[PDB]
Figure 1 (cartoon, rainbow over the protein chains, first blue to last red):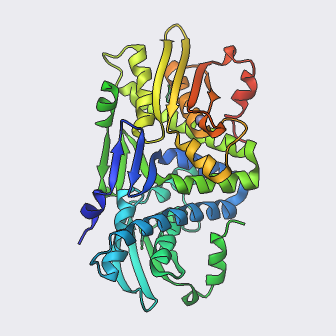
Figure 2 (figure 1 turned 45 degrees about the horizontal axis):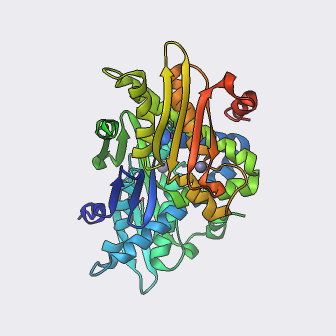
Figure 3 (figure 1 turned 60 degrees about the horizontal axis):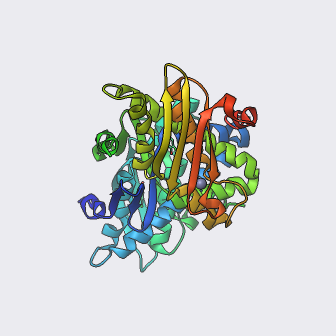
Length: 196
Length: 196
Ligand SMILES: Oc1ccc(Cl)cc1Cl
Ligand SMILES: Oc1ccc(Cl)cc1Cl
Ligand SMILES: [Zn+2]
Ligand SMILES: [Zn+2]
């Protein structure tokens, strides 16, 4: 049920070069407390609104790259088994523990409906460290990744939103992803992914 | 290098918890392209000088945290051996391949003069690809890390600077670290490490 094995062969640590590679993308290992401190400076000086955009887009770029890696290992993987490489990649990257609740996907037909549980999210625990409990969900980067990955996989914009978030006192995160036009505020969610 | 083998044992993947740990500090695997894209947005909107400080301070926090890890492993190690853990962790994290050249350290005496070679500096590759060759050295986060690691380790302000940088088109990066007092522009360099 897990593709963590098939996708781990794609992860090379080259200690005698000082580089890490996931597929054909170079990675770094970064301290979450380092990213936390950057988030603090970004919210404090740019506001929660602008800061959230910067992270969602960073997240978006990451998800799109991992969709590219997923596409190369298609061979005979169903649409769903294709989709599932996203949550797998998220875990391996140590961002969060992803659990697909229910997923309806057809790539050819442009149909997608997806719900997930986000157990153990760094962003959530990182936001809490730096700001305490939040009024709105705080897994920005993580949400940008889901949007980026799924959109690049479908060839059309799939936006995600957190229906529940540990950053808001909840026990875990709960997220929903579906085509842009099935969101009433979708035009305005989509503006969050635009640099400027 | 014995440091790389001993320290690499401190890194573990706990996928059940969707987590990656280096010692007692949680880590994520992040695409350098995603970080590069954030660097570009921050430079485009806040300008080079302010984007530089943000990344230097992010690296600093990283360095200070790896220093806390090296300290727990302070046994049987000379002052040099403990200093060497910084370069090793930086390399393990895939940030850059670090070659210590000459290192003069005595922690109890407050003695520190350190020169280092950097190859494959992610900060250098990512900057050139988003901005082209730069005028001044471009590996902000990497310098912040050496500064934070060594200051934490020495118990006093050690500042680092690139005398050469691939982001300026040189074959490599060359780094000098030494106490605040021995830098001509020392006070101005210390300024970059404080928020706004
Ligand atoms: O965390 C995730 C990463 C990729 C996809 Cl498609 C969904 C989720 Cl919840
Ligand atoms: O890249 C580095 C990491 C730690 C220390 Cl002490 C020096 C350097 Cl140049
Ligand atoms: Zn959340
Ligand atoms: Zn450099």
